[PDB]
Image (cartoon, rainbow, N blue to C red; front, side, top):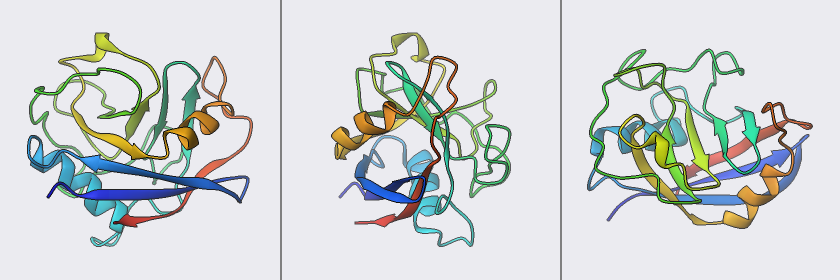
Length: 163
């Protein structure tokens, strides 16, 4: 009953593959719904065509800034920002999907997929989903990152939606 959404990833416009995610609507319904709706575009804006602007191998891929493409933008379906819903779920290993933020109660549209256990983020960032299929595609994306996070090719969400 939890929703599944997919991203089709491209690298300099060339298809790479599909990643799908389970969203934990049962535990973080408000946060899950924001990501789901941004992935379908049903509110008139969302992730389609946006890039992953920061990829640090052995740590995480970060995306979701569809307004400024660099980590300074984005917005939620509720407004510019929304509250930290709860911290029930933890950063337990690769594949975890969690919200980026700038301080308490500043969630927007930016998120990251962890490619390692990141336990120091527990209680600071809201975990709301997990990669279901295509972890190998995340691992492939990671190869286009660098220590400072700049990507060597443009990694975009070429299509997305709900499965």
